[PDB]
Length: 225
Length: 100
Length: 50
Image (tube, rainbow over all chains, first blue to last red; front, side, top):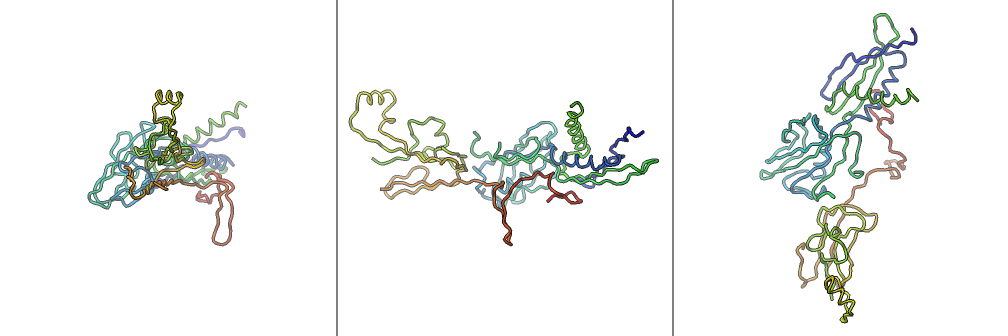
């Protein structure tokens, strides 16, 4: 029949890297490949949720425009480094991590105190450096879940609490391609391959499912009309 | 008499003096906006005659509120930022405060 | 007649916004007219936007 459309399914998921994946949808009718791909790319780049650092406290600092003795980086550079920290929170929408370090050497994400509900996906992420043997740093890092970009200006606090702009989007880039699919006995079906590059804090399949759910929930308003 | 930099501004409330230290100067690292007090200063007004109304006011609200004006430094409207540095210059022979 | 002087320094951060002036090194100046979301920018075969 001409009023019945073959519907796609998730066929292949390839993990090229921990932050790089490919997802295969097959089969698709004529013209549906690009139609689904563009919408999925927009939704994935716009509406994915994630966890981000929002507030920082350091014992010896009062504001972001100062320096700490024994630390080679300024407080602003430390905050910028912390902005790029990738954390997967699995039990709550808000958590506080503690970092304690002392001695000469790099202070990275692996020095953060272990928590049951918090996973660090990149332990090698360098946070700062200690250049003095009798130098120690202790900080408290507030991480919470959201979506999109929230500058600290848009959102009284005691002196010493530093705000950082939140970028909750885990997706770095999205690409898609449409190829000719090889179904049993037809040559008019396509296959959609979505290449996804993220920060390693979200599963590609659940991201695709969440994007599809968002699209369906937004589209259900046009069904009744 | 001389003008004094001090924390005792009688007319303003308790909250408006929350970001000033014991010497009447804003803390380092405070977030300020338009209208916030940075340095608290009082200008003396002097009259040696006390009318009965002035005596009643002094008795009820204290003598510090009287014979004193307000000339504190405030952030201009439309100006915001973080206090990162404070410098105090004092004339020779004058007593230095805690901040200096 | 001057007893004391107190100087206070305030630091602020300015972000980019429409109305700011940008320029190159070849006399090509201009004003920012719009901040476009990432999914609306043109992209290449690899999905990298400009």
